[PDB]
Image (cartoon, rainbow, N blue to C red; front, side):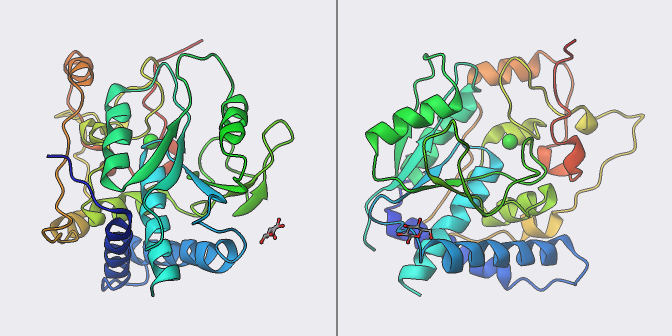
Length: 295
Ligand SMILES: OC[C@H]1O[C@@H](O)[C@H](O)[C@@H](O)[C@@H]1O
Ligand SMILES: [Cl-]
């Protein structure tokens, strides 16, 4: 039982849940309203600024997907926009690129594979056993796919190296030559959680265990700001409505969380502490707080 959707069905599903999110009744000072505004900006970037210039069909656009929450939100919106642009289906699998590393969480590896099957992506993975820079990995990716003109990148202004980015932007001089398409820059952490929880799509289950940012296995811990302690003020949930009223699937689109990898549960159990899930954090400045101390 691996949930598989043909690409067209996946795109239609994402259009429907995104449209449904946009129809949520919310007050003007709410996280949900702000997320609706962020969705509309993302849609404009893709439908108005991107697709008229580069084809998402003929190989001109590839999607950089690393299984994390930002990439996942962006993929859902990208699929929604493919449906909206072309219908509102000419493609069997969507070209996707993952830069793999030897210190990636096993649960994240599993999730990338699961989601590649779920959304009928055509996954290319760089070689995790090659010692090389990201630019080098993409240079090899361009040699395999020389038709690529632009790459969709799930990154936010609050992320490291996010400050001086724009929605459409050529790569650095030491990269292969393509346009970076960066339609998620204006999203905040709270918007990410709101949309992702409402979508009722499977997400990387590490977030459920207190992780807020998935760095590498050696550095990354559950966020200490989410550690449960009788002597700390309990944390309040900002996404109760989204969870309780999350998008209802049909028979063609049913979903289930996949449990974390055994090796990751062992690492979590060894901490002898419990954490609120990642969506109890909404402060962007503390997103990467869960880290091993280094000099
Ligand atoms: O304007 C950005 C891009 O738009 C595309 O439709 C053109 O074919 C490219 O030559 C150009 O770089
Ligand atoms: Cl993350």
